[PDB]
Image (tube, rainbow, N blue to C red):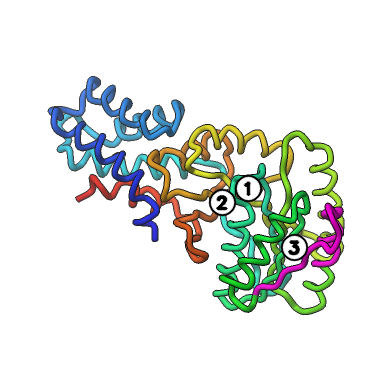
Amino acid sequence: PMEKAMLKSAFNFSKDIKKLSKKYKQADDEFFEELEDVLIQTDMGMKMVLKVSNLVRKKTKRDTSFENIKDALVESLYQAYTDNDWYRIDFKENRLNIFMLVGVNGTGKTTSLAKMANYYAELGYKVLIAAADTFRAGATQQLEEWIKTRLNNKVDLVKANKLNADPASVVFDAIKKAKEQNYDLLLIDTAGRLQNKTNLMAELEKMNKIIQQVEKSAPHEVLLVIDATTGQNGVIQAEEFSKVADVSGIILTKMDSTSKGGIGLAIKELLNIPIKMIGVGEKVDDLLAFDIDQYIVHLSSGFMQ
C-alpha cells in the first residue's frame, strides 16, 4: 500500500535526482545549490529545504560517492521531520475512545471517517459513528451508503431525524448508545467553514461538554483532514483551520494522486502537528497508520536501487 501511495511522488523526486547524478562530480557548494533546487521542487518549503540540505552537507564529504549522498538524503529527510519536541493515536483498550474529524468541507472528512471506522472494526473493535455534520444530509447519505455497502458489521451509525438539526443533539444520542452498549470507539463527523467560526467553535464546545461527562480526557483525538493533491495550498488552509479547533493530529489523504512528496515536511514545518493516518487510495481499507520512515523510504524508492 505505501508503494502504490508514493508511486507518483517517488517518480517525480527520482526523475530529478537521476538528472542530478549525471553531472555529479563532487559534493561541493555548487552541488548543494543543485540539490537545493531539487528539494525545492518537492514543495517541502524553504525552511525544510534549508534543514535537509544542511543535514546532507553535515553527513557527507566532497568525495562522497553519489550512492552515499542518496543514503544521506534519505536519512536527512527523515531527520528533518523527526526534529521536534513531540505522535501516537490515543486509543486504549479499556475505554470508550472518542475521535472527532474536523476540517473545511470538501477535503474528505466523511470518506476518511468511514475508512477509520473500518480500520478499527477490522481490528475487532465495536465502532459507532455520529453523523454530526448536519449542514447537508448529503454527508449523512454518504455515511449510510458506506455502512450498508462497504463497512464491517461492527460499525453502527447515529444520525439526525430532523432537518438541519443541532449537531450536539446527534452527539448526545451517540454518547448514550456508545456508553450503554459497550462500544470501543465513537467517531464524530463535524461540519466546517471558517465563515461560521463562532458557531463552529460553540458547537465543538457543546460536543466536548456532552462527551467529557462520560470520558474526562475526551476527545482523545481531533483529527484534521488534509488533501495532499492540494499541496502547499492545502497546508496553508489546514493551518488556518487549526485556530478554530484544538487539532491533535492530521489525516493526509490522496497521497496516491500527489506528485510532490515534500508535503509531509511542509505539514510538519507549517502546522507542527503529527500526521497520524495516511490515505493510500480509494478503497475502504486504503488507510494506514502514518510512519514517517516508510513515507520517506517509499518516496525515495525510485533512486535507492
> Circle 1 sits on which residue?
224
Quadrant housing residue 9: top left
Image vertical order of residue 120 relative to residue 229, above or below: below
Q: How far apart are the alpha carbons under marks 1 and 3?
A: 17 Å
| Marks 2 and 1 in Cβ contact (< 8 Å) | yes
Q: Start and end of the magenta stretch? A: 155-174
Name the N-terminal-most of marks 2 and 3: 3
Badge 1 density bin: few <14, some 14–19, many ≥20, Cα 10 Å? many
- Which element type, helix, strand or loop, lies under badge 3? strand
Q: Position of residue 141 (x, y in %)?
A: 69, 61
Quadrant housing residue 271: top right
Q: How far apart are the alpha carbons under marks 2 and 1?
A: 6 Å
Q: Which mark is residue 239?
A: none
Q: How far apart are the alpha carbons under marks 2 and 3?
A: 18 Å
Badge 2 density bin: few <14, some 14–19, many ≥20, Cα 10 Å? many
> Circle 2 sits on which residue?
251
114 relative position to 189: left or right: left
Q: Position of residue 175 (x, y in %)?
A: 81, 67
Q: Tag 3: residue type?
A: Ala
Quadrant housing residue 184: bottom right
Nearer the observer, 186 or 133: 133
Image vertical order of residue 231 relative to residue 218, above or below: above
Q: Which mark is residue 130?
A: 3
6 relative position to 70: left or right: right
| Residue found at x 66% / y 42% | 104
| Residue found at x 30% / y 39% | 13
